[PDB]
View 1: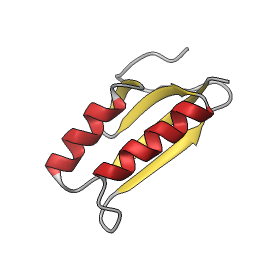
View 2 (view 1 turned 180 degrees about the horizontal axis):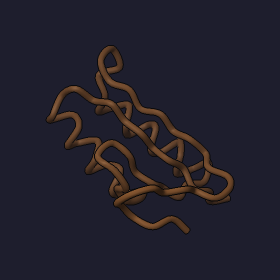
View 3 (view 1 turned 30 degrees about the horizontal axis):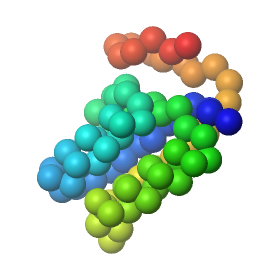
View 4 (view 1 turned 180 degrees about the vertical axis):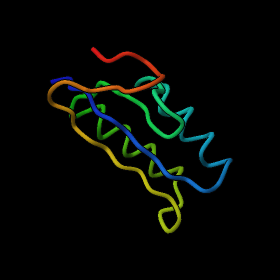
Length: 82
């Protein structure tokens, strides 16, 4: 079912990065400059990948998707964890 994912990206191109961030908003919320937290199940995860693939230059860009299980820990500024 739905689980928390950390979605971290490294996109050198500003235009592609803006498009990717706008896409990620449809699945979750920003937590840091290069990271969103998204609640996804299998179907939404596939949808996210499918749409992210349209946008990325896969020779230059990186996107990592981490399924999270356990307590997220936050030091410093930024959104408090569950």
